[PDB]
Image (cartoon, rainbow, N blue to C red; front, top):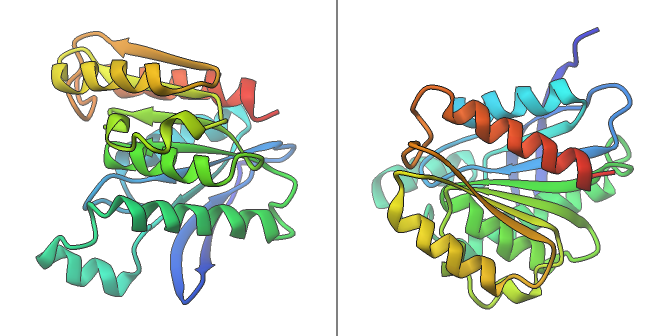
Length: 216
């Protein structure tokens, strides 16, 4: 009936990353989520969005980009949570795992990157141009990954909140650096984490439309 949630261990070289995999019947696309700094696969924001994508018939993989051990150390040092190179490599690793797993090998991979995850998603997408078919960045700072931007081949949707004025101009700047099919959309009167009534729902709705079109 309703799709099942699987607790998976995603191997990326020497590390194992915890994941929550859901694959509705008949799914053709899968959305890999890059959580924001200090967050996890349990993010209520990403879980809400994931449930919306699942309902539209998209598979989802909510993953911890850091190991459990790393999360405990980083909680005090913060020496890993803003390391965009590392986070992108972890996302590339999770992409390869999806590619080589018989349960998901047939699925078209897309990325949903939240806050700092957005930049990490774009850096990873530039590293897997034939594999990653779409990217959505929710309130990110893509402009801070300028070497990756013009190499991204995955159709990219940048979403920002209208009250998050600094991040808007930076997404506008990033949009110009992208050379692929692209769009920037603004959710009016929404702040950084889209906490205002209806904001997060709009993010999910926009992301669903995008992934459904591009992960065919």
